[PDB]
Amino acid sequence: LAADLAQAL
Image 1 (cartoon, one colour):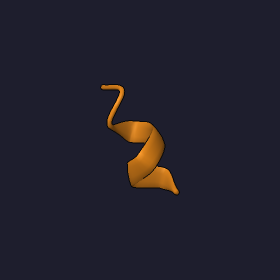
Image 2 (tube, one colour; image 1 turned 60 degrees about the horizontal axis):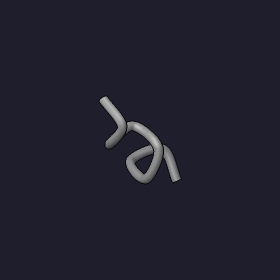
Image 3 (cartoon, helix red, strand yellow; image 1 turned 120 degrees about the horizontal axis):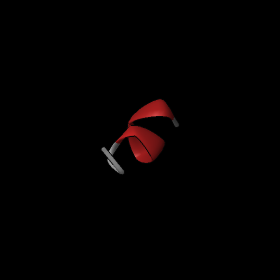
């Protein structure tokens, strides 16, 4: 999940 969110940056 983290990678799925962190992509925003």
